[PDB]
Image (spheres, coloured by chain):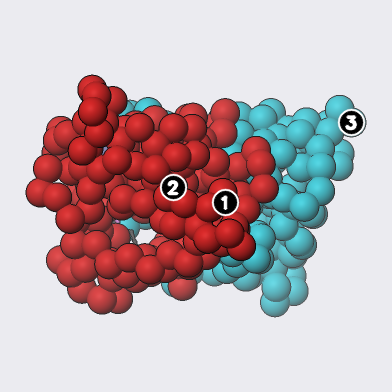
Chain colours: A cyan, B red
Amino acid sequence: ATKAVCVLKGDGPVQGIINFEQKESNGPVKVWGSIKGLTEGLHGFHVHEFGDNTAGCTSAGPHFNPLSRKHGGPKDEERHVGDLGNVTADKDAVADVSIEDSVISLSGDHCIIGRTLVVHEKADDLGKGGNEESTKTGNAGSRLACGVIGIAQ
Amino acid sequence: ATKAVCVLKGDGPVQGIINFEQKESNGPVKVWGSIKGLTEGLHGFHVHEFGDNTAGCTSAGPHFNPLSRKHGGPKDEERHVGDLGNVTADKDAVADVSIEDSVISLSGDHCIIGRTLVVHEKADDLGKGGNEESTKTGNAGSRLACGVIGIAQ
Ligand SMILES: *[Se]c1ccccc1C(=O)NCc1ccc(OC)nc1
Ligand SMILES: *[Se]c1ccccc1C(=O)NCc1ccc(OC)nc1
Ligand SMILES: [Zn+2]
Ligand SMILES: [Zn+2]
């Protein structure tokens, strides 16, 4: 089993810790942890192409998209590898994260280690928004917090 | 060519940006950038095993040592893969970093992507010190700043 971890930090109140575990090289990745400081509602949750935080979360570039697909939701065939959908925050400003994903990996060409995890301002419309940006970013807006995905013990 | 980047931050004023570039997968890695807020003199400069910053730089674990060797300097055959020696700060509290290393890589099994770069409190004695810890840590002391090494554009 392979493990990875991401510490989410930004310029505002949003802070979190996200764990990744993959039991088998061909297998689903469990994604879990907690994000605090979020406004109530949905927040886009994506792996971005670059593990570059030189100038903050903007440096991470677009969604991680090694297969040159359109943006979608995690349950869609047409999605970026980095498309993990939304995390949901309650009035307590906390999102409990508990995801299992079959497209990301911690090995091979879909590997997300060394890329950036980002939590966004607004809801990801999962490419169902009906405008051009829906097919690229899901209209999830600005980047509240991010971190480079690292190898864990 | 493969590129990687690391943003160094910690609990004090030490902050830096380190760039990595490798022209060919089997080839030397150029390491360059700047670290500010350092005390004048040598500071141990290492890649640590885990890209885990959960509880700060301590979470990164020991020096990256895939070959189970003793600690050394970058010019030594007997070294950890993560042993990049020292960066030197002047009275201006800045270290100009300019390293070429043949043992680290950004491709293949000695890859440092997803691991943590750490700048240390004290000088690394490059395993030439008068004690047991010299062969493990180089006596470079506590971790001033660190970051996860990410994939760059
Ligand atoms: Se998966 C990946 C992405 C980018 C760079 C390097 C890797 C990688 O697989 N190699 C290092 C690695 C990853 C995970 C573990 O688990 C213990 N060991 C090494
Ligand atoms: Se760095 C490493 C170690 C073991 C397996 C695979 C890798 C790897 O480098 N893959 C991810 C990667 C890194 C850099 C770039 O640059 C475009 N693309 C993919
Ligand atoms: Zn996407
Ligand atoms: Zn060492």
Q: Which chain letter matches label 1? A: B
* Residue behind mark 3: A91
Left or right of residue B104, residue A17 in this image: right
User: Spatial distance from mark 3 to mark 2, Cα to Cα?
Assistant: 45 Å
Residue B120, x across and y down, in percent: 46, 41
Write down the chain letter for disc 2. B
- What residue is shown with label 2? B43
Q: Nearer the viewer, mark 1 or mark 3?
A: 1
User: Furthest-top residue in view?
Assistant: B132
Residue B82 in percent (x, y) is at: 29, 46
Q: Residues within 10 Å of mark 1 (few under 14, many from 20)?
A: many
Q: Is residue A117 above or below residue B49?
A: below
Q: Quadrant of residue B15?
A: bottom right
Marks 2, 1 in one chain? yes
| Residue depicted at 70% across the width and 77% down the height | A132
Q: Quadrant of the N terminus of chain B?
A: bottom left
Asked if labels 1 and 2 touch by Cβ distance under 8 angstroms, the answer is yes
Residue A114 lies, in percent from the top left, at 43, 53
As drawn, the label of residue B38 is 1
Q: Determine the residue positioned at 22% across, 53% down.
A: B74
Q: Secondary structure at mark 1?
A: loop
Q: Amino acid at mark 3?
A: Lys
Q: Residue at x 62, y 53 (%)?
A: B37
Question: Looking at the picture, which amino acid does disc 1 mark?
Answer: Leu
